[PDB]
Image: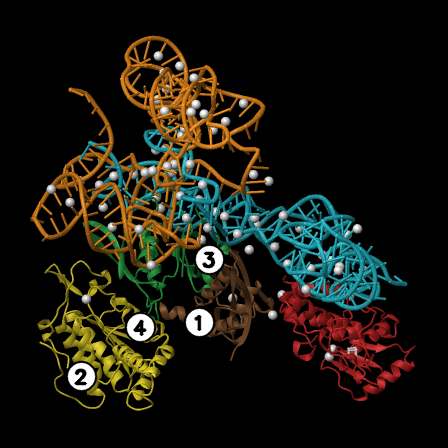
Chain colours: A yellow, B brown, C red, D green, E orange, F cyan
Amino acid sequence: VKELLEAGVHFGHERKRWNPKFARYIYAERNGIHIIDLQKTMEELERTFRFIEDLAMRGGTILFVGTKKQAQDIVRMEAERAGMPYVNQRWLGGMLTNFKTISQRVHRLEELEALFASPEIEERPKKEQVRLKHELERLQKYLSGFRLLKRLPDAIFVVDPTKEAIAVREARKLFIPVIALADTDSDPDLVDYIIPGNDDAIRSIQLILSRAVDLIIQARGGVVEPSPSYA
Amino acid sequence: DFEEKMILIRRTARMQAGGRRFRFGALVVVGDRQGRVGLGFGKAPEVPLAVQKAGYYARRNMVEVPLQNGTIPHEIEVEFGASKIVLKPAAPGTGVIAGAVPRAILELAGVTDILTKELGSRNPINIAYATMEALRQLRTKADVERLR
Amino acid sequence: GRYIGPVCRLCRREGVKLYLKGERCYSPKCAMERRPYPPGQHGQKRARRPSDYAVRLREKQKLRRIYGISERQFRNLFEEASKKKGVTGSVFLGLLESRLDNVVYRLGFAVSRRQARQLVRHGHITVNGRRVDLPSYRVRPGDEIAVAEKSRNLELIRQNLEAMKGRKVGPWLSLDVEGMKGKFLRLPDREDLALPVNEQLVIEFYSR
Amino acid sequence: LTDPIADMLTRIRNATRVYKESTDVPASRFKEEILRILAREGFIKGYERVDVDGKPYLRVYLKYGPRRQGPDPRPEQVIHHIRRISKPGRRVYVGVKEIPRVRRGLGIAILSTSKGVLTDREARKLGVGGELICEVW
RNA sequence: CCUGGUCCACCCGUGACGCUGAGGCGCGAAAGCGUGGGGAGCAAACCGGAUUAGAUACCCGGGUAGUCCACGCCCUAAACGAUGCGCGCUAGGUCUCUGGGUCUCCUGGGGGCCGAAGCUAACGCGUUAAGCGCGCCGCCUGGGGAGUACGGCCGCAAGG
RNA sequence: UAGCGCCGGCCAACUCCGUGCCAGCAGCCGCGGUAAUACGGAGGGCGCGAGCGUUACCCGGAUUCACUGGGCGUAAAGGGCGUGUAGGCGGCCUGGGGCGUCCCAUGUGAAAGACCACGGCUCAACCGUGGGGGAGCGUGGGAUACGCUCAGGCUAGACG
Ligand code: SF4
Ligand SMILES: [Mg+2]
Ligand SMILES: [Mg+2]
Ligand SMILES: [Mg+2]
Ligand SMILES: [Mg+2]
Ligand SMILES: [Mg+2]
Ligand SMILES: [Mg+2]
Ligand SMILES: [Mg+2]
Ligand SMILES: [Mg+2]
Ligand SMILES: [Mg+2]
Ligand SMILES: [Mg+2]
Ligand SMILES: [Mg+2]
Ligand SMILES: [Mg+2]
Ligand SMILES: [Mg+2]
Ligand SMILES: [Mg+2]
Ligand SMILES: [Mg+2]
Ligand SMILES: [Mg+2]
Ligand SMILES: [Mg+2]
Ligand SMILES: [Mg+2]
Ligand SMILES: [Mg+2]
Ligand SMILES: [Mg+2]
Ligand SMILES: [Mg+2]
Ligand SMILES: [Mg+2]
Ligand SMILES: [Mg+2]
Ligand SMILES: [Mg+2]
Ligand SMILES: [Mg+2]
Ligand SMILES: [Mg+2]
Ligand SMILES: [Mg+2]
Ligand SMILES: [Mg+2]
Ligand SMILES: [Mg+2]
Ligand SMILES: [Mg+2]
Ligand SMILES: [Mg+2]
Ligand SMILES: [Mg+2]
Ligand SMILES: [Mg+2]
Ligand SMILES: [Mg+2]
Ligand SMILES: [Mg+2]
Ligand SMILES: [Mg+2]
Ligand SMILES: [Mg+2]
Ligand SMILES: [Mg+2]
Ligand SMILES: [Mg+2]
Ligand SMILES: [Mg+2]
Ligand SMILES: [Mg+2]
Ligand SMILES: [Mg+2]
Ligand SMILES: [Mg+2]
Ligand SMILES: [Mg+2]
Ligand SMILES: [Mg+2]
Ligand SMILES: [Mg+2]
Ligand SMILES: [Mg+2]
Ligand SMILES: [Mg+2]
Ligand SMILES: [Mg+2]
Ligand SMILES: [Mg+2]
Ligand SMILES: [Mg+2]
Ligand SMILES: [Mg+2]
Ligand SMILES: [Mg+2]
Ligand SMILES: [Mg+2]
Ligand SMILES: [Mg+2]
Ligand SMILES: [Mg+2]
Ligand SMILES: [Mg+2]
Ligand SMILES: [Mg+2]
Ligand SMILES: [Mg+2]
Ligand SMILES: [Mg+2]
Ligand SMILES: [Mg+2]
Ligand SMILES: [Mg+2]
Ligand SMILES: [Mg+2]
Ligand SMILES: [Mg+2]
Ligand SMILES: [Mg+2]
Ligand SMILES: [Mg+2]
Ligand SMILES: [Mg+2]
Ligand SMILES: [Mg+2]
Ligand SMILES: [Mg+2]
Ligand SMILES: [Mg+2]
Ligand SMILES: [Mg+2]
Ligand SMILES: [Mg+2]
Ligand SMILES: [Mg+2]
């Protein structure tokens, strides 16, 4: 499952826009660029996946965090493939720390599902349709992956702990383990299970996500061959 | 469940056109008198809700005090901004010698025997915070040998 | 001197029955049993929560008004136990107990401590022989406290020993009824005596 | 520089507050005696005489606790506290009888005595006093 | 022309010769003073015109000390970074000035900004600490009375 | 024989009338301008008790002179800046001494008082008997890590 042709996909980026805590996972600066010791990536995959694999067979949910436009679509395929929740658009404040309240806003979604599946009155004003439809069209935009989540995840898995510091912040306050693919602009000490790698190139996001999705499905009852990606 | 005590209840005001409009706050400790306390601070439009709101936080932030025959294991001095609290271990028949603030905090924590002293700003809310963070920094011989 | 006044107003304030008479304390003509609320114009109003200081004074007068004791003697007896070795609380109770005027009453020589005083002050009591008319004597282990022979034929002490025929008396005391003599075995552990009082709080009253 | 010991204790205290693996102090037979106790009593892993750019130093291997769950992952310290007592400004000595008990036993006090560098315990066993160098917990 | 501090590179010389600093001594913006010059512009005082209830001001026209030079006094300040000096330790990004290199950049020394840890009552400080430490000095102890009075020393006086 | 202080918050104890910024209360914040638990009386209540209150003074609360145990950017607080006298303070290695420092043995540290036990006055106050010490200084012996001194080296501080 592990693989070594990762250097055929990322080895890292971003110059002196670095975070000094990450130096322990950096090989050298060549291309005017911080370069990640890929060896140092394997070590942490071994330990991180052990967590994920051990987390797999226990039948426990995982929240998928990626919202930079470089990792936007690629998380949506993969979280569904493993049948687990994600956030694609905005990470709402209090998704975790205020779950019962945020998820009180999925009950409005599930309730819209039914109402627009006929009939429960269509003699409701034309303009109210206009209003309700768009609201469904609005709600749908954000919550499509969060709706699966019906309880606090036993872990969360992140693309950018720097870009999604808020997510990381809530998880911490809820003692939830934090997992993340994360490059040198990020804060290492902040993540429990670290995948020290490029977090912007779609290449790198595909390799590390999918193979982690596969490790999840492998120990969660079955296996399957390849998954969708743009070249 | 725990034994619960309201230590502080205050009214504060804010200003806008037409005059002042108030808001209330309650410092509340809660504990089992057997090694577990928690301090919560609740603010609300009316006294009762604030007292209840407070209680929920009190349970939301707790701490485990290593009682040894009803006294704390070692000296602790702790500062919280300009507030300082001294907690000093005390022998059996001593009693709990503290101001009504750290008194109720330590009391609900099962502390039966202790010498204490408040130094610096004795502001009720801050002396509270300093008493807690003192407990949260209490250690025992076990805890020490395990670290080192 | 001592308190020497209306005594039911005392229990009514304390919220608890203190056994300050004897006979009437048990009948339903007892004041607490008719009115369990503080004496005077404002007793039936709904109370307001007492402050820490309010609470402690009240626990103190409780233990104190039991004994019919002056604050000075109380304070000094207390400030003894504060100095002397061990746990303060027990020793204070202990030294409180070793009072003759108390000892006489715990034995059932008298129906009240107030009567146990008039028994002591009128010489009707004796300690290991010698006449003693001092309510304040600190009775020590091994002491035998008895009635004077020259008064032993008195209605009150005979009638009051009548109840005592097989009556229980605390573990540290023995009693030869008819013979009119009792014995002090030792000063109490807090267990032996169940005064309706949280004794730690009295220390804290004085820590102020 | 006016105080080697105070510099030494301090070089550490800064290093432990941001969890460095080690840090180096300029070498002295007296610092070796203090690090020795600091080694044995287990506030540090241990130390070794290295050399920096031609100059003698002591490299001291720091020791900490475990990662913590929560908003602040930063592991507990092993040296919570370290500070000079006796200083060049105000020399501090204690007779045997007034030797202090640091933190109700859970800590130590290092000494300079005519029998060598000893702890509060040791000094009381050997029966000697000395200049109270510092305190640690 | 005469002269001071200061950085850099070489790692050549001395071998703890160091740090601080009560008194002392010197330096010390402006205004001010003494004797003598100088005086274009500017301008306290002062005159006049406006404004105004008034206008001993703000605005306009004039104008003397002074502002400049030499020598000698005065020694004060929001004399400020409202931050005594020295040393060691504790992430980094960036802009700039100035040496040196193996001239991407590396290394020293100064000048700014943002920020790690930490500090802070907060504001903010943060390798130019207001952080963690040592040494020595100066200073604070409720507002006013009062930087006044008295004494004392200094000054031509102002006054310090 | 039972008296005296208090009942707005601190701080334990509340009602009616009388007064109307008057009369008066007051340790501090504050009370009194027609529904005053704050003034005067009464009832009731709280606290002590042959006592209770008041004035004055001493320590405490005051880590508010800070040795324990504080501070100086904006709260009170860095000297306007240098230079330097006394003084305080000082790097790495080795030896002599043993001044500071630590230990041991001894002398002194009177009696009363303090404390612990016991005992005598019916208890207690009071008093008796015994017990346990300490610093600090004199003397003898010992210790040598740190600070001291003397001596001999070093080059990381400092100067050239
Ligand atoms: S009767 Fe009830 S109230 Fe009156 S004294 Fe006896 S016990 Fe106390
Ligand atoms: Mg990135
Ligand atoms: Mg614990
Ligand atoms: Mg502070
Ligand atoms: Mg405070
Ligand atoms: Mg103990
Ligand atoms: Mg204060
Ligand atoms: Mg206060
Ligand atoms: Mg009873
Ligand atoms: Mg209580
Ligand atoms: Mg005791
Ligand atoms: Mg009883
Ligand atoms: Mg007291
Ligand atoms: Mg000290
Ligand atoms: Mg050389
Ligand atoms: Mg000078
Ligand atoms: Mg001048
Ligand atoms: Mg001039
Ligand atoms: Mg003039
Ligand atoms: Mg002139
Ligand atoms: Mg002229
Ligand atoms: Mg004019
Ligand atoms: Mg005019
Ligand atoms: Mg004019
Ligand atoms: Mg003009
Ligand atoms: Mg002139
Ligand atoms: Mg002039
Ligand atoms: Mg300036
Ligand atoms: Mg400057
Ligand atoms: Mg100034
Ligand atoms: Mg100022
Ligand atoms: Mg200075
Ligand atoms: Mg300073
Ligand atoms: Mg350059
Ligand atoms: Mg160049
Ligand atoms: Mg620079
Ligand atoms: Mg400039
Ligand atoms: Mg800044
Ligand atoms: Mg921070
Ligand atoms: Mg910088
Ligand atoms: Mg400050
Ligand atoms: Mg005054
Ligand atoms: Mg004044
Ligand atoms: Mg003057
Ligand atoms: Mg002046
Ligand atoms: Mg004068
Ligand atoms: Mg009184
Ligand atoms: Mg009182
Ligand atoms: Mg009250
Ligand atoms: Mg009148
Ligand atoms: Mg009225
Ligand atoms: Mg009053
Ligand atoms: Mg009244
Ligand atoms: Mg009397
Ligand atoms: Mg008197
Ligand atoms: Mg005083
Ligand atoms: Mg004091
Ligand atoms: Mg001090
Ligand atoms: Mg202060
Ligand atoms: Mg200055
Ligand atoms: Mg000057
Ligand atoms: Mg100087
Ligand atoms: Mg000198
Ligand atoms: Mg010297
Ligand atoms: Mg030295
Ligand atoms: Mg020597
Ligand atoms: Mg010597
Ligand atoms: Mg002696
Ligand atoms: Mg004596
Ligand atoms: Mg006797
Ligand atoms: Mg003593
Ligand atoms: Mg030697
Ligand atoms: Mg030499
Ligand atoms: Mg050099």
Is the C-beta of the residue carrying label 2 under 8 Å from the nearest atom of ligand 2?
A: no
Residue A61 lies left or right of residue D98; in this view the side is: left
What residue did someone put label 1 on?
B61
Co-location on one chain, circles 3 and 1:
no
Q: Please, which chain is the residue tagged with disc 3 on? A: D
Amino acid at dot 4 = Leu
Q: Which mark is residue C5?
A: none
Q: Are marks 3 and 4 in contact (CB under 8 Å)?
A: no
Question: Mark 4 or mark 2, which is nearer to you?
Answer: 4
Q: Position of residue B92 (x, y in %)?
A: 58, 69
Residue carrying label 3: D127
Residue under numbered circle 4: A92
Q: In the rendered structure, which amino acid carries the disc numbered 3? A: Gly
C204 in relation to A65, above or below: above
Q: Secondary structure at mark 3?
A: loop
Identify the secondary structure beneath mark 2.
Answer: helix
Please report, as a chain letter, where disc 2 is located.
A
Q: Position of residue F118 (x, y in %)?
A: 73, 66
Residue type at tag 1? Asn
Distance of mark 3 from mark 4, alpha carbons? Answer: 67 Å
Question: CA–CA distance between discs 4 and 2?
Answer: 28 Å
Q: Chain of mark 1?
A: B
Q: Are marks 2 and 1 on the same chain?
A: no
Camera-side residue of A34 and F147: A34
Q: Are marks 3 and 2 in contact (CB under 8 Å)?
A: no
Q: Which residue is mark 2?
A: A214
Front-lying residue, A39 or F145:
A39
Closer to the chain start, of discs 4 and 2, is 4
Dot 1: what SS?
loop
Is there one chain holding both mark 1 and mark 4?
no
Kindly report which numbered mark, 3 or 1, lies closer to the viewer in this rendering: 1
Chain containing the residue with disc 4? A
